[PDB]
Amino acid sequence: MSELNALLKDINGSLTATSESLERLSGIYSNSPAEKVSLLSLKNGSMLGYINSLLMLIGNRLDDECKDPSAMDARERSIQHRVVLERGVKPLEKKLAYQLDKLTRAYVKMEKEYK
Amino acid sequence: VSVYQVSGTNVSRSLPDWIAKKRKRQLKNDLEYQNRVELIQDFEFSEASNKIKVSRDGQYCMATGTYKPQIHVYDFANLSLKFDRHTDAENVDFTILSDDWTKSVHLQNDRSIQFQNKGGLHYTTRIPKFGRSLVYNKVNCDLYVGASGNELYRLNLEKGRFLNPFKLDTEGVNHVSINEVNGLLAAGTETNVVEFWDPRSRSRVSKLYLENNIDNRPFQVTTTSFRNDGLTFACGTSNGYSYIYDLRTSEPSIIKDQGYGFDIKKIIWLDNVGTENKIVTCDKRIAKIWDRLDGKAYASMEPSVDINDIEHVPGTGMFFTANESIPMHTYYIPSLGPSPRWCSFLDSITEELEEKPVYSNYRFITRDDVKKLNLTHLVGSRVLRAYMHGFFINTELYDKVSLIA
Amino acid sequence: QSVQRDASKGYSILQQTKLFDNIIDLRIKLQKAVIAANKLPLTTESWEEAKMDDSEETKRLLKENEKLFNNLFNRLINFRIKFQLGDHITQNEEVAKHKLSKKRSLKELYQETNSLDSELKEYRTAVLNKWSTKVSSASGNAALSNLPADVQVENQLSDMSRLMKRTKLNRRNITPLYFQKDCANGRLPELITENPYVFDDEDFYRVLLNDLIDKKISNAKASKGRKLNYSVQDPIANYEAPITSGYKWSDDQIDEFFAGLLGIQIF
Amino acid sequence: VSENFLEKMMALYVSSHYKNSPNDLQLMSDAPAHKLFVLLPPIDPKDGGRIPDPLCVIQIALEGEISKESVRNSLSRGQRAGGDLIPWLISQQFQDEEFASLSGARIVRIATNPEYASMGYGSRAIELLRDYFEGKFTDMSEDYSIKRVSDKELAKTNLLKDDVKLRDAKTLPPLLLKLSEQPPHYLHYLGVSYGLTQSLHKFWKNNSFVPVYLRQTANDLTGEHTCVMLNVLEGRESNWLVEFAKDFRKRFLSLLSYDFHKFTAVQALSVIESSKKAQDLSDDEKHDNKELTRTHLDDIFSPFDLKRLDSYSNNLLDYHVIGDMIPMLALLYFGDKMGDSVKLSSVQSAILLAIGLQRKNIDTIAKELNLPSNQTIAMFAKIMRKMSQYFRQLL
Amino acid sequence: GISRDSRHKRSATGAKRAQFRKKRKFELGRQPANTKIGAKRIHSVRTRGGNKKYRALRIETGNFSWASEGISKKTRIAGVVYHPSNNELVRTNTLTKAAIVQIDATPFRQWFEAHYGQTRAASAKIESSVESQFSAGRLYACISSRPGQSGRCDGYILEGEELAFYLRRL
């Protein structure tokens, strides 16, 4: 059994597993006035884009032609998303971490009181 | 922190103590026998010890033995057994009503409460169902007896009358305890709940449901202890988890786990010794001293034999442990506090003392629990250090794997 | 009334925090694809030889791989448009709805990805500037006036070359299929251990995993006495005397304390 | 509503003080540097905005930001300007010009309800007050100045017709402001001045303040010595506090016999321990204690002294004969030149401190510590046995 | 204090008898032998005559007999599960006669494999419940000795109608 055959099967298992789990994540988001934290909303979007850039590297490599085996454009997109998450979002939410925990605790006590 | 075992068997755990007595005649020539020192004469039960407690005056102590069920009373001043008194049954729990040893009450295994005076046994009364704990409320002078059934038994000493029994939602009372600050009574139920009761009236102030995320195994409240501050409250579970609660809030401030998964037999609060923020939790194998605020372990007590009960001498750094061995063990921790007035010269021999010193620091996990947590792949790695039949892991990592599993 | 806004705000915070845990789970499942993908060939000849090893089976797997990949990424872009729509990241609602309805090709999907990244970048600049100003005012740094976070994005994005080298580092020591053959034939211009063609985000993947592990922990008949008798027992009569002093606390404090047992514009 | 709240705040403020004077009310209202903070219970929405009673009230005074030129001029002339007590006092007690320039806030008063005392409200309020000035209270919600009476209004009104009314409710800000709403002033340190007692000293010890100065003469009214104790916020330089704490320690030990001999050994140990916590705050090794060298040991003690030290460890000597070395030994040990080799218990340190530094007799120690005299002597011998062994180890 | 005399009891008619004499040595009782699981502890008791009795404070091993296989093996006692008289003894894991206990199957399992060469076939056939107990690793046994008298905790493996009845009770 060829090495490529084992590899392509592995991608097929990963892609279908991710797709089913993507189906679940989309449903809960669709299920969800409530206003979200703009920083935390951005934190979601940046790392979500990081996965697409990773998947874009998957797409560039999967193509039999491999015109861009390095996947530079996918590389750059992943870099931009990764760069912002680690050093841009993280220090700010560390400053905001104390206040965020207070509100989440504040909601939890109310929910316990209601029940 | 240096811990000294002044009295107690000094043989390996595997070797039984009764052979220490056979070799005794053989080893009498050995110099070590001449040098070894007992603190108080005649501290041994012919088979074993159940419970130990010290007088409030601090000059007397009393203990109970398996067979022939006996009640030794020892005077600290004279370093001698004041007297032995035999009982018709093995004792479960007892309290000293008087400031001295003169007055005491014993709850035996035969469903009967014994009222022992200085002269001798005074009267015997038999409760409807078997009892597991006994506590005395000084203000109202009523004895509440924990029971296997739902109801908590009430006996009033002033009137010599059995008053109505408090009714509990859940069956089985393991431990009962009273806060002298407020009068609140906490009953340790078999189910994972503690019910809090008002003494003046006859009502349940509230019921606290204990929750442990780490283990889903059902657990039973084994012990309850209040502070002289009136604010904070400790619970011992059958899973070896000790919860310290500020009673005002439902959440647990600190959860400390002992390591061997055994029940917490006793919780002692070291307020009087100095550095009030210290607490002792006692299991079958280890009694650990640790800080309420930091949770850090300060000293660990690891006797060669199973512990049945532990007691602290107020204002001093020692602990009397009722064990399954023939001799009961007396321990000394100089850093916590000084020796008493009666062991004035114990200090001089601290170098000659045994100076017993990982096991308490880390988490003991059996081989089966390793299989449950899917940690078999880590066997042989530095993460899991094998001791006896179990692999020791860090407390922080144990919560990590348990939640994932 | 302000409690309701705080509780609802906590709900929104919780919803988002769960969303990270779901998307990181998406990353975890995709991890083996990235490891596997980095092991694939790099040149046309290597791919052709890989197919020549098993022509029929490889062709079938390739067709399924293309179908699953296209279906998955189209759904991702649909989620991206909806996600960036609901969170006000994209302001043109009509255009977003039209994109969702229409079915897109691989090249068209690439156009959306370039776009969706572009609005995200604009939203990125506005959000970082806003919060960085807020924290600066909150911490008194406004009184003082430690770079702005958005400026930090510009600076380290200016340092492209350094971080590209970080990705190119081969920590796992992955060797793509027929790598030696491509090297010998000179089909790999960039190379002519750090390898440009293998992508390594192991530390970033681990850091996210350590963070995910961390949050989970922090969040985590009269005979024998069987019947009761209330009659007086003389021997125990007056066995002890009650203490007249009573509890150290006052009764009012105890009653207050038990009740707390276990739970012009003024403002 | 404001008057009722003002009464409740004054009720708590006065109760904590022994004899409060009416002058303080004018100081609270008009003094610009002062700010008021109140601890309140959770607000039930069902109560319709009814003000809850205050549990803890903190009065702070912003101090510092002093021009270096003024400090040198004031220091040279020996004249103390009004206000900014801590900036002046530490400046004179350390002659450090940079400190006066540092911005800080003095906790003028903390008051807790006597009925609710010891429950932890006083500590909890300080914790947030520390957190607030640290900036942790960032705004979560997506002006508070009042227009003054204009000069045009003043000119247009006559005495007979003048209408003096309470300011319109609309113009006024809210009585109670959320922490997030108002930005905090950038501060370097938090300072407290108080009379040193066991219960009170323990309180700031738990709140991570560091002593820097103790006043030598006892206050006549209270018989108590004033203590100034400081805390550095995160994100701000902490080196200066460590240097002051080290210097205060050396100042503290020497002065124990002079005037502080009255103090209990436990308290002197407590004061030393509070300072020692300050060095633990500093992870830097740049400033560290130096171990006693062999040459320094030789200068301090002669070889006859060391033999005399050894014999009493062997019990071949009496206690009296070794009275010579005790004060130097206490200075060296508490100076930490002894090093990690020889550590002692709290009881042992108290015994060694007093005889070495308070100069108290061994019998006096037994009474103060509620121990037998012979036990104290036995403890003292073991302490020195440890020190004798280290000297052998050094040699 | 323990006495076995019938004089203190009331008559069959219900009459309250009076004391005839002081209590005698020959009609006395001894304290209960609450044997429990643990490291072996036994002490002797001097009884009437020169005869001695052995008191089982603690015992963790016992010689249990597979009657159907006609054998006896010494096995560690795991714990008490059911006692027909009082359930408090079960809760306290007190060992007495007739108590139902759980024992290790290792020696019996090795014995079965050693003779029958099986983990001939007709003889090797055993009751399904007992084989299930082998699979579990712990065997239900009934104590046929009196630990409070002889100091022994011997027993036999439950089988057949006894096993079915005790499983139903469990």
Image (cartoon, coloured by chain):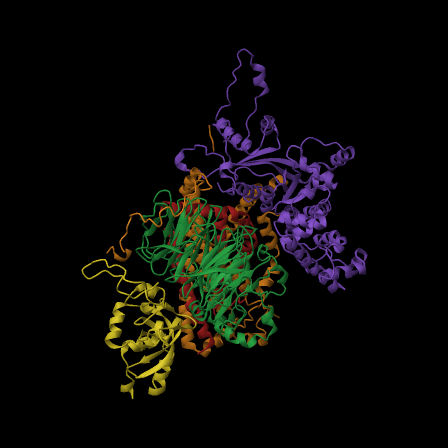
Chain colours: A red, B green, C orange, D purple, E yellow
In which image quadrant can residue B130 be found?
bottom left
| Residue D290 x %, y % | 74, 56
Instruction: Specify the farthest residue to the front.
Output: E21
In which image quadrant can residue D217 be found?
top right
| Residue D99 x %, y % | 70, 41
| Residue A2 x %, y % | 45, 77
Looking at this view, is E130 or D75 the one in front?
E130
- The reply, left or right, for residue A3 in relation to residue D203 is left
Looking at this view, is B251 or D390 the one in front?
D390
Q: Is residue A65 visible?
A: no
Instruction: Specify the farthest residue to the top.
Output: D160
Q: Is residue B368 above or below residue D221?
A: below
Q: Is residue B40 above or below residue A40?
A: below
Report how many numbered discs are placed on residues in the image. Answer: 0
Which image quadrant: the C terminus of chain B?
bottom left
| Residue C158 x %, y % | 61, 54
